[PDB]
Amino acid sequence: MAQDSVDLSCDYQFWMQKLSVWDQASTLETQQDTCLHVAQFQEFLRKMYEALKEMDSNTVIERFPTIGQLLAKACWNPFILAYDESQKILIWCLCCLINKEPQNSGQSKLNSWIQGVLSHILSALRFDKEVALFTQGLGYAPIDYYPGLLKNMVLSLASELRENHLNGFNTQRRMAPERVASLSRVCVPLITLTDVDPLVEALLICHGREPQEILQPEFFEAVNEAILLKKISLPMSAVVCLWLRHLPSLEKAMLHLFEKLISSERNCLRRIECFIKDSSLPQAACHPAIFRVVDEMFRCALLETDGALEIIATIQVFTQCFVEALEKASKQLRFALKTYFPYTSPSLAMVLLQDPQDIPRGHWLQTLKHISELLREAVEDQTHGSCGGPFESWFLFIHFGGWAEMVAEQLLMSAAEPPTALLWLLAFYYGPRDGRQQRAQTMVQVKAVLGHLLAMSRSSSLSAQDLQTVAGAPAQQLIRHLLLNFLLWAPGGHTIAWDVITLMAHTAEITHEIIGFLDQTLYRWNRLGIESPRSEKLARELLKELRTQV
Amino acid sequence: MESLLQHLDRFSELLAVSSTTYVSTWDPATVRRALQWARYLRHIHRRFGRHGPIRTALERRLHNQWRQEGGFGRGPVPGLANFQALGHCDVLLSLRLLENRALGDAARYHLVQQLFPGPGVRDADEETLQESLARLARRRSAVHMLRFNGYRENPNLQEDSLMKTQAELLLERLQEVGKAEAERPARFLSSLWERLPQNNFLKVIAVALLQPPLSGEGSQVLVHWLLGNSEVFAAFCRALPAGLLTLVTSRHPALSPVYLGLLTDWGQRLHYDLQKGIWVGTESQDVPWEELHNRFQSLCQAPPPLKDKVLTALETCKAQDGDFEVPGLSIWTDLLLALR
Amino acid sequence: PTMLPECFFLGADHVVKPLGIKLSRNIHLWDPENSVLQNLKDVLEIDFPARAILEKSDFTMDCGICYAYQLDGTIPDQVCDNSQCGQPFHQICLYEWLRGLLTSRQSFNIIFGECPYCSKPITLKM
Amino acid sequence: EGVEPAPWAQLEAPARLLLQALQAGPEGARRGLGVLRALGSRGWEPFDWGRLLEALCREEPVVQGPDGRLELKPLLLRLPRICQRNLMSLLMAVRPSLPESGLLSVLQIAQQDLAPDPDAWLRALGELLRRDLGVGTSMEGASPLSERCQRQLQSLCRGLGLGGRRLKSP
Ligand SMILES: [Zn+2]
Ligand SMILES: [Zn+2]
């Protein structure tokens, strides 16, 4: 109960003076301008609809001054009347202004004018003359040929574009580049019209030989947006070529993935996996150009946070999807891995690509122990002919889930006399760029902590305070996560998990982090097919209750 | 089956009078009854509209309706044109009522309220009437925009996009009359030829003669109609461009010999004047040298089944008029020379 | 060089899989003090042929435009009329290529043009 | 009037074939590798990159902007826009076996300093190629991305709990 007129009475004058500037978009500049502003116009009309619906016609005169001129100007512009719902709302506004029982001649004139403009929308013969004449003879109404004609109109145009593509450097008939840009502007307001989809796919695949961009960026954005909300459903080759010709559209698409992992679906990796596979990014990222730019936006996010676990998991999912699509669809002549991951020793990647589904559960220790050795070489023995640094070898290692998370659980499986190389790998995970004094201090703390935990596990089901003693910093998240892995692993868990979780969940950030952790872990288990049903049911119940605290 | 006859004919009568300017007595009661009937028909088309005696029975009823009316004199009312239009009969009626100025105010209001309740019923199982009319406005605007921003009149008419839709309409109208078998296609074509603009019709015919079948009974009927009626074929081969008629003739060998007779006759009614080095006709409507050269050049630049035929038809007309070997004496010599 | 190489497998999906598995199991056994061959042989746990066929190597029988066998049912059928090329093609790839070049001219169902690899007269009948 | 010859017309045939191959859309890049192996196969087993990387910088004239304005464009900006982005992709793929002096002249073109209406993909592949030499650290805010996306991505990462890891170094 605050404004009710003011913002709207301003927007009214803005839009009315703009419609007056526009009307019918018979030029270039009116067209580009309409296609831009149209989306807001739609919202303006929804608000206007709400306003006129709640009240009634012919009695009140609030904005009845120029509502007529506004709706007319709107209707004769066809880039407005072809956008998503504009027409349906414009009908509604005129249905409200009608009157059942006119008294003064103004109400009758209004109703007549309304019938006139509605008829112009629905049923006016502004089309070619001879084609109109031909049909009446055969006894056809507009409706029962409009569809085929459109269909047959579209296919024509698509062929011409198809032919212009093959005539690259040929003495004939060059499709005038003005018309290609024109079509690109005309497809934009009506992308959610199913009858035109054939035209889009042809425009995107038929790039042409012209070195300048012949399509205008209002077109790329509309297609891109519409692929991501699933309102157009193109085929994959079209979206890959859109990504490859308009890099700011690939940024706006990969940001729309980061909103998916930050806002809507935090730490539900099944909905992220579903989204990524359904989106085409994995299929598109088989192209080295797109994987270097998609990977660069992940790095920017990896640095802005100082190693957020939520980003890491998304990267792991993405990389797992990407792998079985690089594999799936490049039999002979595929790109060499130093071309996607160009900084590290290729050796290392070649190791980390090997899926742990393929390996027996018992031989994971050997493989990790080897990887650790080669990673230690690549970071600490930083000589020429190697990585750029520790961060880069880290950023690689992060891409491959499976390996990075099984580490603690293998230390617990070999908790008696932990191997120092695994301790090294784990300490390296939670912090690189530390220096040996830090890494050593962390490792010896961790070894002492593991000494405490093996003793506590082989003991009975004990309290949570005994755990806060050893927990009691820069090395907290490592110990926290190791202790959570201990809870899920040890059969002493499922009794005292809550006692530790409540105390550990100081803030909301640690809670969210632990939720993420547990989701990642169950995703990882269900993927690798490694499971103890105690931990599965335990983690599911804990996750259920922690999703309530938020 | 019999239950549907009195329904469908009644609906067709109500629809036909809908467009007519007698609308005074109409009310929300009439319109509601109309739209509920239309709902029933739209449901029928959906339920058991394919592959049965019911579909064909209804087609029989419809086409008999459209031929007892015919479309001459008392009213050229469309009516619902064909079985597919049952699936959108309700839209047609509504559009007609919006066009009838004589509609009363309370009727119009109830109507528009039943088409456009608002987004109160955004969730609906059956694609309702409001969505249908919005989707119609969308298509209409899309068609206008393509025409005025992308579309170009292709020269090879067969591949153009307006003509190719007209063609397929005509072809559907021949197939329906063939299956009906009530009156012969020749009658339909003759009636068409008088009513509507002829040059347009002819362009259309050319392209309809080339569309592949969609079941070649369509083309097979038109060749017979044309060979029956010479005057049109006189204006046919006179109006179209060259390459089109070349593709026509290679497609239909039945059209080759007569067309050559037509050309041969236009040659024989030219005379050469020595002062300007050009064959000319006496009368103005006799095809000039250039057009006749064009057509023969198109005919000769064709598949070999026609090349030998036209070439032999020309040589026999040369030798017929004295076997001269020098220009100024025989149009047929000047053609055979202007080919090498 | 002596360090582990990038290696992967082309061929029959049923033959390669056990090889990938065996590789996965033995990759820890790689050692950059021996030779590449002397490491690979005990890693993949198999021996090599020393030139099993020297004459009839896999003469690449792929499109030489799209580099695939089996493009949409079609086979590499259209070939080069040349002893030094002999390169097969597909109808579709080789049609879209020849319709591009400036030199090419089209009769009724025929296009004459230059073979992409050797630039000799090649004919394509649709 | 409107016949244009292909701008790679005058080059040694092998380069002509490579550039012809890359033209063919996004699967354009892959094809390039098949082309290079299919010329390792033929009589000239080595492929003389140094000449293609010279020829890619050579300039010719064009008339763009208003109607009349003479400008000199090197080859790399004059050949079709999907060939550009799949060339630079295939150089990213085979960087190690290229002479650096030529490569640098190309990147020098790619950077497109003070051009208005640049080709964002050419610039970003410039920068990612520089980064792969390492001689193009550049001491800049020279990132592959736009400033606009990086700002909205900072804007987004802020709504997430920063981690106990230490990756950025003083
Ligand atoms: Zn092929
Ligand atoms: Zn060859």
Image: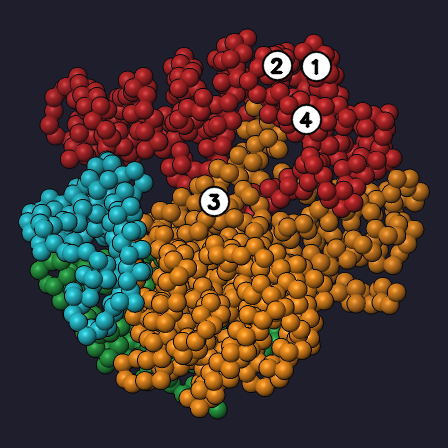
Q: Which residue is mark 3?
A: A198
Q: Amino acid at mark 4?
A: Arg
Question: Relative to residue A120, is residue A275 drawn left or right?
Answer: left
Label 2: which secondary element: helix
Callout 1 amino acid: Leu
Q: Give the letter of the red chain.
A: B
- Which residue is identified by label 2? B54
Quick check: B192 left or right of A462?
left
Q: Cβ–Cβ below 8 Å for labels 1 and 4?
A: no
Say if mark 3 contacts mark 2, CB within 8 Å. Answer: no
The residue singled out by tag 4 in the image is: B42
The residue under label 1 is: B4
Residue B30: percent from the left, percent from the top?
Answer: 83, 25
State the separation of the CA atoms marked 1 and 2.
10 Å
SS assignment at label 3: helix
Q: Colour of chain D?
A: green
Tags 1 and 2 in contact by the CB under 8 Å rule? yes
Are there few (<14), some (14-19), or many (20+) residues within 10 Å of tag 3?
Answer: some
Q: Position of residue C68 (x, y in %)?
A: 26, 48
Mark 3 sits near ligand 1, with its Cβ under 8 Å away: no
Classed neighbour count for the residue bearing mark 2: other residues with Cα under 10 Å, few (<14), some (14–19), many (≥20): some
